[PDB]
Image (spheres, grey):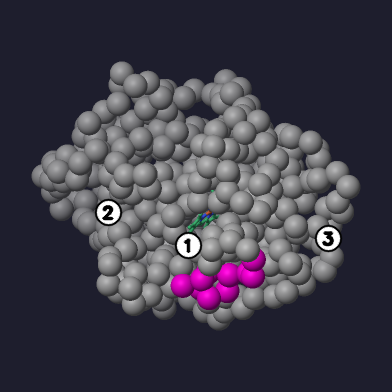
Amino acid sequence: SLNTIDIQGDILVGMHKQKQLFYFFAINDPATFKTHLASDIAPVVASVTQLSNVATQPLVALNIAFSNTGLLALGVTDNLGDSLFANGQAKDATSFKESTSSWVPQFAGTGIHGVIILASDTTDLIDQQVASIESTFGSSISKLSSLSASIRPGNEAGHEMFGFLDLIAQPAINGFNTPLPGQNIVDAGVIITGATNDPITRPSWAVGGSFLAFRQLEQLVPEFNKYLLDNAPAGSGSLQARADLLGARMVGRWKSGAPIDLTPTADDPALGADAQRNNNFTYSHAGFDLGSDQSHCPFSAHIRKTRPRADLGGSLTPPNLSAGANSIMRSGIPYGPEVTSAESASNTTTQERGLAFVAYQAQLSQGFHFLQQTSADNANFPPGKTPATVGLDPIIGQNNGQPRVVNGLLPSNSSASLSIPQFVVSHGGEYFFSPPISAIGGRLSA
Ligand code: HEM
């Protein structure tokens, strides 16, 4: 059975707070650090059970995860069963056709030992917790870098910086979640190390944890907006409506959350808002060839790249259950200032904003790394299409800084190709292990 009292809350349900801070640290003195890990951190680590009850939301929700070098620092030399985690994300950068030369320097190495995720409805409360941690740990912990993040304001709450409603679609864990129409249903061990049908043997103390892939992804919002206007397909509606259609073709959903597969020519804001309906699709349509039909949703659309559904086989009617092992739980949150008037007017980014991307999975090679390398960056994925060259994911696909060729986006002609500049720019990140809560004051403090 899944022991959710022992699982850190961000993994399965998110922090449920307006503000987050990602505090990236080194461990200078493992003896003193361990003492305070047990006494000061472990008691305030928020569990899935705690965060799932409206009566037990803490003022500051706190989670903590460790990199490979952070575990080594703590004298933990165990094999957690994940080569990508052990090697660190910087060594993995080439797999995604990017260079660490573009990264925040602190990420371009393995000096980061962990991340504390602090979440609260105000930054003042976060800052107070940080001050407390720095006081009680002294120099045994040291801040290397940090990133502040926030839910976006007003009617954009829950939307990412490009304006799209986010975190709609997640895997349902069999026995834990009540599945929604269309939602994939997966074994707990796809997300939680050592849980049901995780095929990789783990250290005993690590059962109930998950690997956290962190990415600092800058978004070029004015540039994206202008691109859509400049490349809007011809049609009867306003120019902006036609630009909106192109954006929806790139993401696979309208900004409202309505999936284009179910409403291919216009938004349906009521559909987007309804969790019982907004995921109820497989990409299959009777009387259309799945291998060639891009009239409902392009093969290159972001969500189709990241959850192929019927493109990888399985049921043509909902729920499609394909590629469960390639599922990730997402807890990303936007960062940076809102787009200013001047930036919008000049169509030019002058301040850094984007997504503090957080993905959880039990195997990095099957989750984040797979989705980036085998799908988003792969012009021939999904397989079996006609024509075969799908092109890259227009949102996250990478090709060493060059414009991405993306096919199928234009409804009038599925063979029409666009060469699209990057609108998402990686500043790097790291792979961490979020341990079960018992390990925090247990093995890791021993
Ligand atoms: C700044 C970068 C990104 C932006 C703006 C973005 C935006 C979005 C949006 C708007 C959706 C639709 C909402 C939803 O279906 O929940 C979505 C879905 C999703 N994204 Fe991204 N995303 C980004 C990065 C990534 C990365 C790096 C990955 C993985 C390598 C990823 C994986 C997914 C997955 C798995 C889904 C759900 C697919 C499904 O289950 O149908 N995203 N994203």
Q: Which amino acid does label 2 sit on?
A: Ser
Is the C-beta of the residue carrying label 1 under 8 Å from the nearest atom of ligand 1?
Answer: no
Q: Badge 1 local density, few (<14 within 10 Å), some, or many (20+)?
A: many
Residue, disc 1: 89
Front residue of this view, candidates 286 and 405: 286
Q: What element carries label 1?
A: helix
Q: Answer few, some or many: residues within 10 Å of disc 3's Cα (few below 14, many 20 plus, some between 14 and 19).
A: some
Q: How far apart are marks 3 and 1 (CA)?
A: 36 Å
Name, please, the residue furthest toward the bottom.
Answer: 402
For the residues labelled 3 and 2, the Cα–Cα distance comes to 43 Å
Label 2 secondary element: strand
Residue at image coords 61%, 51%: 266
- Residue 202 location, quadrant: top right
Magenta segment range?
Answer: 226-235
Q: Give the percent coordinates (x, y) of residue 122.
A: 20, 41
Graded by Cα atoms within 10 Å as few (under 14), some (14 to 19) or many (20 or more), the crowding at tag 2 reads: some
Give the CA distance from mark 2 to mark 1. Answer: 21 Å
Q: Which of marks 2 and 1 is nearer the N terminus?
A: 1
Residue on which disc 2 sits: 148
Residue 77, can we see it? no
Residue 273 left/right relative to 17: right
Q: Residue at x 81, y 45 (%)?
A: 285
